[PDB]
Image (cartoon, rainbow over all chains, first blue to last red; front, top):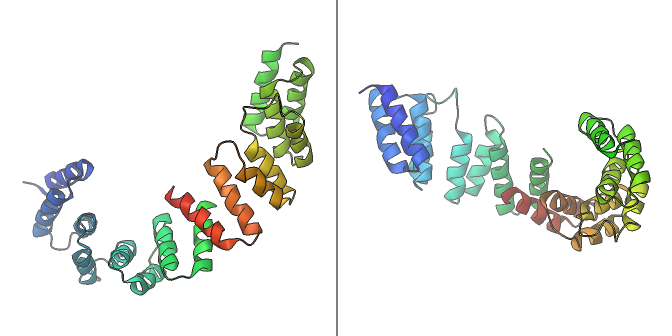
Length: 130
Length: 130
């Protein structure tokens, strides 16, 4: 009945691999708080894992003020990349809040797809020679 | 006097930090055993760590029978690379016993040095996807 009981079900289904029943749970947590910031993150992660890139992207687009403290540029870039919106995914990655090695690897891929192969080399070498 | 006391002293310096003293200890082990395959391997490693690339390369080039069935190609290429004998390092790598990741990363670096950028990029991408 309690919200922390549901988060335990999210992580059971998450570790299990069942991302559809994990999304079911995450929406119940969103029924409680329609702006639970951890819930909005885990919705996107599930939706991305289900191939639902256009709606996972939609969640992030209509929750900017709510997600200002933790902006999800990587999830957005990725969503845009998988939908073949490469120039979009480039804008997202270069604005991106904070750098990670997964954000860098995606920047590489975007530059590879844009035939910008010297910039891409630098990204991939940086990555390998930390 | 005893050999397992020396093999313990190598490990003390080697795993700690010092490789100058670790080198002399290994040459004590080589007075006794003429062609100790593990001591020859340790000489090469210690020599490389001291920047004595000509020497290490010569240890390999004149102990090819004794140090056979033994992955020395990376050590050999690395020495060639650090001596700015890039084409030699390239050949050493391209004929190498058993390819590995660090050997792959050196191959990339060797191609970058030859301005063979497109092949380089391929190597670094392959390395990041594994």
